[PDB]
Amino acid sequence: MKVVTGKSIKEVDKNELVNILNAYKKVEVDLGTGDGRYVYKNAKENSGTLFIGIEPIQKQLENYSRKSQKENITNAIYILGSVEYFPDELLGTADKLTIILPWGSLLQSITNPNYEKNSLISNILKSNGICEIVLGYSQEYRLELENLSVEYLKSTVIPIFEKNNLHLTEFGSLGKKDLKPIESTWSKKLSFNRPLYQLKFKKM
Image 1 (cartoon, rainbow, N blue to C red):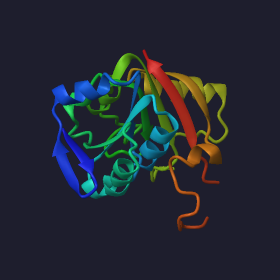
Image 2: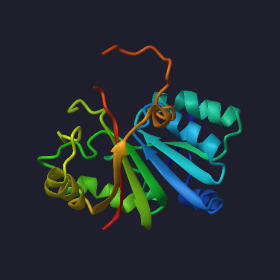
Image 3: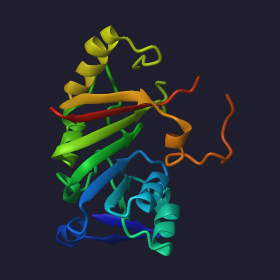
């Protein structure tokens, strides 16, 4: 697989990756982070966990992979990948998988899901792994979560994800304390109720 460090990429094979994974008690794979900020911020806060960001365009991960290397944040690693070109080396490695949608074709449609494609989620995870999905960024925001009722939860939300081998364990709103790892608070953005949601699952 191809590891990003600034303007450069370098091949790391499975044998080398195994030596890296084995040094940590927890491994987390992070998809959809935009520029890898989430990987850097969480690595700095949890030195015992290895955080792995995967994005398809090398320039996406240039800034934070360089920051991580310069600041000796050795538990943050950044890898080229996508649904269509996913690194086999990372299958079965994650104690936690966090998906900040969108990430390409992953979970792209609620009405015609590519189940063969979405099976990546369970196959990244270890058997007792946890998946966290942050919803609200996709252009479709579709799931109507603003005024969640037990009927909609049981008849719509839970079945959509059980069809991808995910059993829902937690649902809730994101707060500004939780946005900070994902997004800069102060960077220039469009002005505009813009809610974001966090859903956690275990394997079925």
